[PDB]
Length: 56
Image (cartoon, rainbow, N blue to C red; front, top):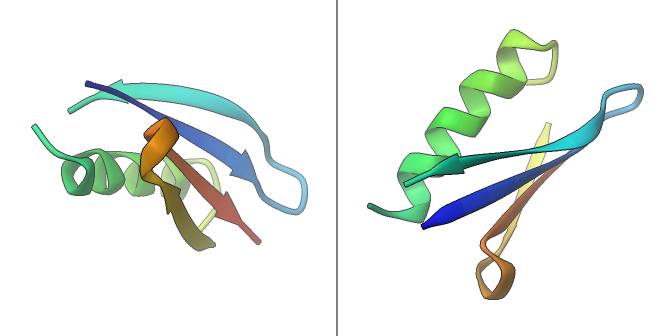
């Protein structure tokens, strides 16, 4: 399935998507993406919309 990431850092805002097996693998990929763009963040997930949000 396609999972979505919502970036809601203090300055880093945006959305991006990735394909995954399960949600946990998508989370690991998204966390690396966020890290490479300056956000280490508080992570939440809405399974109904297959959407992760990372907040600072």
